């Protein structure tokens, strides 16, 4: 297992524009297009993202290309962020993937807001971080996904994904 296989399980793959769990237009492997209620705005962000006139449908290669870029961007956002970088640097390789998964889902700013959890993660107080991570809108809106990510932080293994 690695970050790619993990996020592919968590996000799925859809080749036509769809609404994510928050109701936002999305494509591919959780690639958010726009928070705007307009499908036309979404189609326009999609064409711009892909570089061709898509009419709301992309190929598998194209979905995986956006996915590669988004994973890359999630990593870059962690390393650029003063609150996220030291936590990531402190973590082993499996728990690093859990942090990338959170940033991919909710963005660098959203994750940087988990001040107390991040501190516990840095201190390697795994059971405590896991309890604090769960007291969140994130956990109450997407409990199954959040539980898998939290379990990864708690155990440092891929057991929730196997
Ligand atoms: Cl893009
Ligand atoms: Cl979920």
Image (cartoon, rainbow, N blue to C red):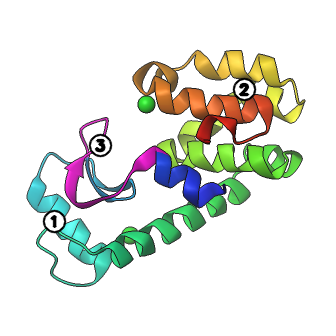
Which tag, 2 or 3, sits closer to the chain's start?
3
- From the top left corner, tell me how far across and down residue 123 is, in percent: 90, 30
- Which of pointers 2 and 3 indicates the residue nearer the eye? 3
Q: Mark 3 and mark 1: span between their CA atoms?
A: 15 Å
Say which of 2 and 20 sits in front.
Answer: 2
Residue 28 occupies which quadrant of the picture? bottom left
Residues marked 2 and 3 touching at CB (< 8 Å): no
The residue positioned farthest toward the front in the image shown = 162
Query: Where is mark 3, residue-wise?
Result: 20
**Residue 43, numbered label:** 1
Query: Where is mark 2, residue-wise?
Result: 117
Helix, strand or loop under label 3:
loop
Residue 115 occupies which quadrant of the picture? top right
- From the top left corner, tell me how far across and down residue 81 is, in percent: 69, 52
Instruction: Give the residue displayed 33% in from the left and 73% down from the top.
Output: 60
Q: Quadrant of ligand 1?
A: bottom left
Q: Which residues are magenta?
A: 10-24
**Mark 2 Cα within 10 Å, few/some/many (few <14, many 20+)?**
many
Q: Mark 2 and mark 1: span between their CA atoms?
A: 37 Å
Q: Quadrant of the C terminus?
A: top right
Which tag, 3 or 1, sits closer to the chain's start?
3
């Amino acid at each position: 297992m690695n970050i790619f296989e993990m996020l592919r399980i968590d996000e799925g793959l859809r080749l036509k524009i769809y609404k994510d769990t928050e109701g936002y237009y999305t494509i591919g492997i959780g690639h958010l297009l726009t928070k705007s209620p307009s499908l036309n705005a979404a189609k326009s962000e999609l064409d711009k993202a892909i570089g061709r006139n898509t009419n709301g449908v992309i190929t598998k290669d194209e979905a995986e290309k956006l996915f590669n870029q988004d994973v890359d961007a999630a990593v870059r956002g962690i390393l650029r962020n003063a609150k996220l970088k030291p936590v990531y640097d402190s973590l082993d390789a499996v728990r690093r993937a859990a942090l990338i998964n959170m940033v991919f889902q909710m963005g660098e700013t959203g994750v940087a807001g988990f001040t107390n959890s991040l501190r516990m993660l840095q201190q390697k107080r795994w059971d405590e971080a896991a309890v604090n991570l769960a007291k969140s809108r994130w956990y109450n809106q997407t409990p199954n996904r959040a539980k898998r990510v939290i379990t990864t932080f708690r155990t440092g293994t891929w057991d929730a994904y196997k």
